[PDB]
Structure formats: structure tokens, C-alpha cells
Image (cartoon, coloured by chain):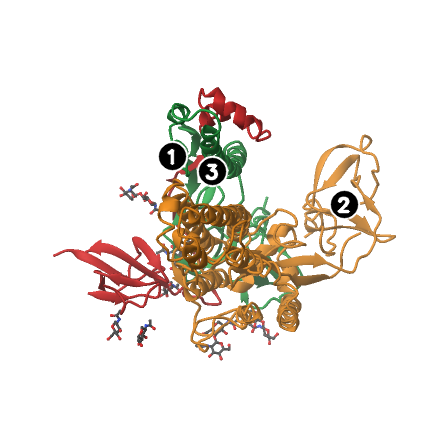
Chain colours: A green, B red, C orange
Amino acid sequence: TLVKQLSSNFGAISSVLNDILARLDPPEAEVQIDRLITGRLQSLQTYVTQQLIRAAEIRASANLAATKMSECVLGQSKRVDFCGKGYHLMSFPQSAPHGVVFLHVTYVPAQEKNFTTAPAICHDGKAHFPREGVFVSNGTHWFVTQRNFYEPQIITTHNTFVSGNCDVVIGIVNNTVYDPLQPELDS
Amino acid sequence: GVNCTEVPNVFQTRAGCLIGAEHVNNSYECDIPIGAGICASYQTSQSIIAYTMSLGAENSVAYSNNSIAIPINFTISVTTEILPVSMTKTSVDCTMYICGDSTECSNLLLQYGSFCTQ
Amino acid sequence: AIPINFTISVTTEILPVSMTKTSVDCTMYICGDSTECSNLLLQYGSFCTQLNRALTGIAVEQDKNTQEVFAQVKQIYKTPPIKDFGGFNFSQILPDPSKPSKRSFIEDLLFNKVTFNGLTVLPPLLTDEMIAQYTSALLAGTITSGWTFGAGAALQIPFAMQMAYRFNGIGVTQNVLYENQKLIANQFNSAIGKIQDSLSSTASALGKLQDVVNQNAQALNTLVKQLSSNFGAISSVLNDILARLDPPEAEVQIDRLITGRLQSLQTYVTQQLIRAAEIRASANLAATKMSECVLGQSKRVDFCGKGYHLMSFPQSAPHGVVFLHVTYVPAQEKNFTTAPAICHDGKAHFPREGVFVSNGTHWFVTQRNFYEPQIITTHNTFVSGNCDVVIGIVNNTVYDPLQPELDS
Ligand SMILES: *[C@@H]1O[C@H](CO)[C@@H](O[C@@H]2O[C@H](CO)[C@@H](O)[C@H](O)[C@H]2NC(C)=O)[C@H](O)[C@H]1NC(C)=O
Ligand SMILES: *[C@@H]1O[C@H](CO)[C@@H](O[C@@H]2O[C@H](CO)[C@@H](O)[C@H](O)[C@H]2NC(C)=O)[C@H](O)[C@H]1NC(C)=O
Ligand SMILES: *[C@@H]1O[C@H](CO)[C@@H](O[C@@H]2O[C@H](CO)[C@@H](O)[C@H](O)[C@H]2NC(C)=O)[C@H](O)[C@H]1NC(C)=O
Ligand SMILES: *[C@@H]1O[C@H](CO)[C@@H](O[C@@H]2O[C@H](CO)[C@@H](O)[C@H](O)[C@H]2NC(C)=O)[C@H](O)[C@H]1NC(C)=O
Ligand SMILES: *[C@@H]1O[C@H](CO)[C@@H](O)[C@H](O)[C@H]1NC(C)=O
Ligand SMILES: *[C@@H]1O[C@H](CO)[C@@H](O)[C@H](O)[C@H]1NC(C)=O
Ligand SMILES: *[C@@H]1O[C@H](CO)[C@@H](O)[C@H](O)[C@H]1NC(C)=O
């Protein structure tokens, strides 16, 4: 568009400047050249202004790209949905023509399956909560998995702790909590 | 944006008049956007069809007070993201663009202050 | 100093997301229904289709924004019939069957607060019902599924456990919740109502998205009010010049008017172009404040509201979006003497995750943000070395659980 604006007329009798200077010597060449100069100058100013605004856009995007390359690549961002959709593992940058491209590796849980649960467990009066994990039941027995992977294992005292008495927790469930120390006592 | 009784099947949208597009009654993830929830697309003997866009398949999560779902499997998914970082470094000279080897124009341009240096 | 009690607070944040679309014809504005302004305007070059190309770019991005903000979910979840969520009732942010346009008791008092010359006003791509349905899907997917409807499919989890496993992020344990469920529930209910009161009483908060419609109507007013200005010519009414001066005097007069009107229109387009950059800057902040605060649990400080952020709910608003950050601000304090390490039988028992504190005679090992003092055992402390290098070491006794068991 900036180039094409040169062929325009703007009110003079011609657009090509030499021909104007090749037909009209003393003042009237100048009265036409005034119009030519005004028009061309305004077109140039407009072009410069949108260039400035577009450059601001690009710089905002480039700062975003710099942040992504600093956080996704070198470390391991916990900011959800920042570096990909799911749980972030790694990333591998790739060049691109006037840009950069990332390759977000991501863990994605699937193949769900539902169990009845329980916030805690009474046993001999004291309500046991899980250290890390959740309580579940496979229909008849109660286990303690982790969050994102059904890897059940026997409830014990090395993975559950004690707080108070099961009178205020709402939704308590009876069970027995296994002590590894008891079997190894007859020596 | 014209009540299209006043124009030279024929659908009457909230954003104007859409002539030459069938108003189907089902809903899809839309291809070509128009406005006010109306999109158009090419599908099935073929023709063009306009409708109201959809947002997604319904899902009623069976929420109970003592039930939790725990995944049994994972699946590593690798995706892509593209971002611009720079644009070409273009520079323009004022005097060549405005006058162009035409000193009798540069003398006049002199009077206009300093609309080259900035 | 270690807190004894806590308070739950439900603040508010308001951001603008998108302007109102517009599109201005060139020659209907410059030359209002005239033909003697065809010759006198084809002279100037590609001005018209520059102005008619910047405006559509703005118009399309102003609608890309509202689709990048609210359309981060993939499916439309719905709650079960009424409610069961422990003691928390979201009975006044959730949609209701009444009021045909599905909309909740808060984003209704938000909509009841901000109540042609060559100018056209195009409609938005997403009507006010579709945004309200997105903000209800994102609301029914977090009340029922927690962290994990942004990762993949939505996994159910009872709400009590959701709120309990959200504390374990900010630092406090889960017993702290389960023995204080009633307190936290009735603190949360009697903190949502203050938002209703504050929003209904005055328009104090919704200024951020009101001084935007109050600024896009100043430029749009000046643009049409500068049609009545001679700009340095005999008249401003086009037909009057067209009639009074037939010879090539109308050329110079109409050139003066055309230059004036073209300059005014160009300086309107430039102002819109600049003003549409900060709107996108705020729309890009809404997207990353709604990915992180809503669909997760941010550990950044002061980002999702002051305090320890643990939940949040989105609520729509006219050309905007409103959050309802929930935080965990501790309360009434005490003061205790402390020690960097105990010293039992030559070694130095550091605390696993906590702080040793005292009362004058006893010692304990508590958390950070609550005061539940256990008893120092070799299940709360890990031994490292000897008892001289540490500065501030104290000497005490450290209980061992297996010892009072061998006797029987
Ligand atoms: C899941 O529940 C099933 C019952 O439906 C358990 O099956 C029995 O578990 C007992 C444990 O004391 C075993 O002695 C039995 O041999 C099991 N049954 C069979 C047919 O082998 C099962 O153990 C539970 N899951 C786990 C991991 O224990
Ligand atoms: C879990 O088991 C305990 C003990 O087996 C039950 O405690 C009962 O409590 C009531 C009132 O405190 C007593 O009258 C009973 O004698 C206790 N024992 C039994 C076997 O009932 C407790 O009720 C059980 N949990 C539930 C939900 O019933
Ligand atoms: C979880 O939901 C079930 C719904 O079945 C609740 O079960 C109800 O319990 C009350 C009182 O115990 C009974 O009067 C109802 O008859 C039960 N429902 C049915 C369909 O029989 C259960 O109470 C809920 N969990 C908690 C902790 O209240
Ligand atoms: C988790 O998903 C993978 C698929 O990615 C399952 O792998 C399949 O396992 C079955 C059973 O051994 C094989 O017959 C298939 O050939 C495997 N397919 C692939 C593509 O690996 C894996 O078994 C799943 N895990 C569980 C516990 O079911
Ligand atoms: C798991 O969910 C399905 C429906 O989503 C339900 O029919 C089934 O009974 C649930 N399983 C258990 C053990 O509750
Ligand atoms: C268009 O004009 C007719 C004439 O009365 C009217 O009946 C119709 O409702 C108008 N269209 C719309 C969309 O209002
Ligand atoms: C869709 O079908 C229903 C059923 O008759 C009708 O009421 C409605 O007007 C139809 N909509 C369109 C766009 O054809």
C-alpha cells in the first residue's frame, strides 16, 4: 500500500514529479509540488504509525515466548494450561522462520474407574487420615492409593496418621489398621 | 444489518440477511462464523447450510457424596505451540520516497521542519 | 507467632475483556450522498480501504478475545438435580431454571448495573446466553470435579475431600478441615452474601468495565460532531457550497472539507487502534488468570486475591468477567519461645516439617498456619549430627514410641 500510494494524484495535474518539473518552471511547479509533498508525507506518517503499533504487538508476543522458553524448557512449570494441556513433563524448542515453536510433552490420565471412598477410619477410638493418598474400597476391602494412579495397598500405620477421636469427622468408616510391629514379636 | 424485505432459500438473521443458504435445524461445531450465534458451512446433492453453533457434548458427572474415580492408565501426549518473535527490519528513506532525485522538490521539503529525522 | 484461628474471605476481581465492534464507511462519511465528491476523492489514494481494513482487524480480534477467555472448557457439564455439597451452598452463583436467559443471582445484578450516519455496530459472535453457558459449565465442573477437568475427562470427588485436599496444598493438614467443617462452611456462606450487598448497594466495583463504554462513546461522539466545522472554508453544509459556487471554486472549498474530514477520521482510527491494545492486554490476563485460578490452585502470591488462594468461581458481566477468589487468612495469634533443634543424647533432632515451640515447661512440634501441638517423637524429627555446631540449640527429651512396648 505504501508503494502504491506513489501513483496517486492528490490534486495536482500529474503524479510523476519529473514531468511536472518538465512542463512548468517558476512558481506553478511549486504550487503543484506542494500538494504532492503533502499527500506523500501523510501517507508516510500513516505507514510509520501502524508499523509502531504492530511492533508493540510483536514485542508483547516475543516477551511471552521468552517466558515460555525460560519456564517450560529449563524447569518444570506447575502453572496449569501454561505449557500444554495436562500435567507438564518437558518441552523441546524448535526454530521457525521469524518465530519459535515448542513441543510440550504432557502426562494425561485416562481409563477411569470409580470406587466408594472415606475421609478417615476409626480404630480403637482414634480417626486415621492418610498421609499422602486417598482412601478407597474395591467393594469389600479398604486401601490407600495415590492421587493419579490406582495402585492400591494395605492400610497401615506407616502411611496414615492419627488426630483426635472419630467424633467430629463427618463420614467416618470403621476398619482395622494393620501394625507391622505385631507379627515380629515372638523371638 | 438490513431487514431484508428491502433487497433487489432466504434466511433472516440477527446480523443481517443471508440469501442463498439453507437454514438447517440441527447444530454443529461451526466452520464459517457470521454473528449472533449463527454460522454457516458446506455439507450435504451438496449445498450450504446456516444454523446456530454448538458448544459441546453434554456431560452429567455422576456426583455422589462417597464416590471417587481414579485413573488406571495414562497416555503421554505431545503437542505444539507457535509464536512469532520478530518481523523483517524494513527501513525507508524520507527524501527519496517523497522527492526522488528531484532537488527542486527537496528545497521545498526543507520548509516542512524536520519530518524526516523522527 | 503462630495462629490459633482462621478466617475465609471471598474477594472480587473485575477485568474488561472486549470492546464494542464498529465499522465506519469511508465515502458516506466524507461525502454524504454526493457525486461531486467522487472526482475530488478518487484523487487521494488507498485511504478508504486502509481505514476499512484496520477497523475489521480490531473487530475480529475483539471477538477472538471473548472466545479465548471463556472457551477453555471442551464440554458442557451440569450439576446433579439440586445439591449435596457438605455445608456449602452455591445457591446464588449457580444457574436457576427461572429467568429464561440462564443466569445466576450475581451475574444478574452485574447486568443491571451498566444499563447512524455512516456508522455501523456489528453484533458479537457469542450472544449473552452462550457466555453464560460457558461460565456455568466451568462452574459445574469445578464444584463437582476439582483440579482434574482441565487435564482430561472430569473425575468426580466428594466436595468435602476436594476442599480438604486443597488445604494440603497451602500447607495445613486435613484434620484441620474435617474437625472444622461447620465453621468453614458457615464462614463461607456468610462471606458470599457480602458480595451481594456490596454490588447491590453501589456501583463502586464495576468501574473498570464502565469507564470503557464511557470512553468508546467519546471518540464515537466527536467523530460525528466534527461534521459541523468549516475546517477553513466558506461553509460546512455540502449542498450549500454545491449550489452557491458552481465553477472551480467548489473544487478548493470541497478539498478543504475533504482534508478536514479525512484527518478527523484517520485520527479516530488511530485512537481505536491504540485503545484496542490495552483491552487485549487485559484479555490476555483474564485467560491466564482463569486457566490458573479456576482450573487449578496457584501458589503465586497476591495473584489470585490476597491471602492463600484455594478456590475461585467465574461470573460473567457486560464486556467483562468477574472472579470470586477464596483465600485463607490466619487470625488471632499467640507468641512462643522456639528452638532450631532439640538435643537428645548428644545428637540434634531437627523438625521434619514444623517448628518447635514451648510454653514455659513443655515443648511441641506444630505446623505453620495452625496450632496443633503434637509431642516430639522420633516420627516427627530427623537426626543429623552432633550438638555443638547449631546456634540456638536447646536440651530437652525426645519420646520414642517403641520403648514402652518391650515390657509386655
Ligand atoms: C478386592 O476385593 C476382592 C473381593 O471381591 C478381594 O478378593 C479376595 O481378597 C482376599 C483378601 O483377604 C483374598 O484372601 C482372596 O483370595 C481374594 N479372592 C480371590 C478369589 O482371590 C481382593 O483381595 C481385593 N483386592 C486386593 C488387592 O486385595
Ligand atoms: C464402628 O464400630 C464401633 C465399635 O465397633 C461402633 O461403636 C458403637 O458405638 C455405640 C455408641 O457409642 C455403642 O453403643 C456400641 O456398643 C458401639 N459398638 C458397636 C459394635 O456398635 C460404631 O457404631 C461403628 N460405626 C458405625 C457407623 O456404626
Ligand atoms: C450420601 O447420599 C446418600 C443418598 O442415598 C445419603 O443416604 C441417605 O441417608 C439418609 C440418612 O442417613 C436416609 O434417610 C436416606 O434414605 C438415604 N438415601 C437413600 C436413597 O436411601 C447419605 O446420607 C449421603 N451421605 C451423608 C454423609 O449424608
Ligand atoms: C494401558 O494402556 C495401554 C495402551 O496404551 C495398554 O497396552 C495394551 O495392553 C494389552 C494387554 O497386555 C495388550 O494386549 C495391548 O497390545 C496393549 N496395547 C498397547 C497399544 O500398548 C495397557 O495394557 C493398559 N494398562 C492396563 C493396566 O490395562
Ligand atoms: C461408577 O459410575 C457408574 C456411572 O457413572 C455407576 O453406574 C456405577 O455404579 C459406579 N460404580 C460404583 C462402584 O459406584
Ligand atoms: C421487517 O419489517 C417487517 C415489516 O413490518 C416486520 O414485520 C419484521 O418484523 C421486520 N423484521 C424484523 C427482524 O423485525
Ligand atoms: C426447528 O424445528 C422446530 C420444530 O417444529 C421448530 O419449532 C423450529 O422453528 C425449527 N427451527 C428452524 C431454524 O427451522
Residue A176 shows in the view: no
Mark 3 or 1, which is nearer the eye?
1
Quadrant housing the N terminus of chain A:
top left
Secondary structure beneath label 2: loop
Judging by the rendered image, the residue that carries numbered circle 2 is: C398
Judging by the rendered image, the residue that carries numbered circle 3 is: A89
Badge number at residue C171: none
Asked if disc 1 is less than 8 Å from ligand 6, the answer is: no
Q: Residue at x 61, y 66 (%)?
A: A169
Residue C160 in picture, x, y percent from top left? 55, 64
| Quadrant of the image occupied by residue B14 | bottom left
Left or right: residue C179 compared with residue B96:
right
Residue A8 in picture, x, y percent from top left? 38, 35
Secondary structure beneath label 1: loop
| Residue at the farthest bottom position | C98
Say few, some or many: other residues with alpha carbon within 10 Å of mark 3 (under 14 / 14 to 19 / 20 or more): some
Disc 1 sits on a residue from what chain?
A
| Quadrant of the image occupied by residue C194 | bottom right
* C-alpha distance separating marks 3 and 1: 68 Å
Q: Residue at x 80, y 57 (%)?
A: C333
Mark 2 or 3, which is nearer the eye?
3
Point out the quarter of the image occupied by ligand 5: bottom left
Disc 2 sits on a residue from what chain?
C
Say few, some or many: other residues with alpha carbon within 10 Å of mark 1 (under 14 / 14 to 19 / 20 or more): few
**Three-letter code for the amino acid on which mark 3 is drawn:** Leu
Judging by the rendered image, the residue that carries numbered circle 1 is: A13
Left or right: residue A118 compared with residue C127:
right
Residue C116 in picture, x, y percent from top left? 43, 63
* C-alpha distance separating marks 2 and 1: 102 Å
Disc 3 sits on a residue from what chain?
A
